[PDB]
Length: 341
Ligand SMILES: COc1ccc([C@H]2CC(C(=O)O)=NC(=O)N2)cc1
Ligand code: NI
Image (cartoon, rainbow, N blue to C red; front, side, top):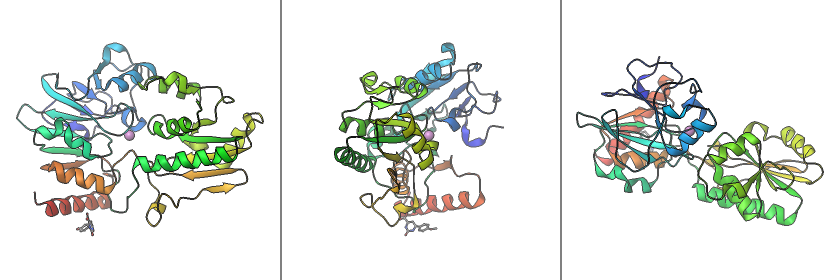
């Protein structure tokens, strides 16, 4: 049964609701972005209209083999009509093709669904500033004051300087970056740029990157794991045993691994700065866990909501326990009292 926080009242619309079969009354299925728990259930035998960004559309067509007749790509920052309802897609600052959706209901109410997002002040200068929002469906992944992490730009700076230093000292060192399906591409593309290298990867990952509208992408990537000093592996394999095994396959081209595991958050952030981050090392392999988040920090989330001043907030993450629900409700109340709305 599709839960209430994936349903848009006064429409036939759902959001990221593809693992429930045919939802009763749903005339259009919106997909905010191509991450697994959000698209889980889509396949080549889906027969209902999907509305999404152009990049998400490319991925549905090529990775999942969804028939072209069911993919409805919409441009960003543009007033569109879907089944008689005005909608706008906004960049979510999450992963390639990820959007937030504004719905303008027939009764005059306006709803913003954030999808997954990392809130930023630049969002204040989009079509969002043009009207009042009555309901907000909010990505509450890190809705607690202990979640601090640096900006993405500080984290990339750290990664670039670390990698450049290691390969300048040892020209036979290899850099490895852990990955999921999409998101955090800037980590490996920025490192490879400073090293003057292409990025080595699996055929399936190569195919994914071809779907993302990155300029000159086919010059930056390869499946040749011997003519590349930056390689991608599944996040699962970023550990001493997986990396030892990987070094064996490269055929005496490399004698050292520097690896990055670009997670969301690690509690070590609490009492330690980005300059202070130290690797785990065993012999010729070092592993850095870096807090490259594609979700809002507590403070980013707070500032966004206090600017928007919604009448009602519906959380879409951490909704499964009484404690979690209660804790989020308390923060929303503090935010409202502080700002005076
Ligand atoms: C139930 O009421 C509260 C819940 C959380 C806090 C946090 C949050 C905060 C902030 O958001 O600036 N400032 C704090 O010092 N503590 C304060 C009151
Ligand atoms: Ni996501």
